Image (tube, rainbow, N blue to C red):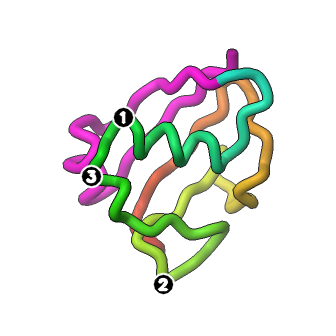
Amino acid sequence: SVKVKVKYFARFRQLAGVDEEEIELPEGARVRDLIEEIKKRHEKFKEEVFGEGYDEDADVNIAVNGRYVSWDEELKDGDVVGVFPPV
């Protein structure tokens, strides 16, 4: 298992119902798998468009340990993933 700390920002704190949450993912999990799991846990995210890396046209951008990454970036145990409106 890979356990990541997800930090939600701004209106996504209301959609998630928490400011942060730990998400355990199977071995080999990628950023795209984490996005699917967020949507599974919190159905209000299904309708939100996630961008890949920096994308001002998306509803949501993510960063892993402070960095924009691809959807196929492999997550590591202890990674911190921010979920935020595009900067």
Q: Nearer the viewer, residue 84 or 40?
A: 40
Q: Considering depth in this image, is 36 or 83 the residue closer to the camera?
A: 36
- Amino acid identity at mark 3: Lys
User: How many other residues sit within 10 Å of disc 2, few (<14), some (14-19) or many (≥20)?
Assistant: few
Q: Is residue 4 above or below residue 69?
A: above
Residue 7 in the image: state x and y as whole percent.
Answer: 43, 41
User: From the viewer's perspective, is 16 left or right of 86?
Assistant: left
Residue under circle 2?
57
- Secondary structure of the residue carrying numbered label 3: helix
The amino acid beneath tag 1 is: Arg
In this view, 69 is above or below 20: below
Q: Is residue 52 left or right of residue 37?
A: right
Distance CA(mark 1)–CA(mark 2): 24 Å
Q: Could you say which quadrant of the image residue 68 lies in?
A: bottom right
The residue located at (72%, 34%) in the rendering is 29
Is 29 displayed left or right of 66 in the figure?
Answer: right
Write the residue at 50% across / 82% down.
56
Mark whose residue sits in front, 2 or 3: 3
Q: Residue at x 37, y 64 (%)?
A: 48
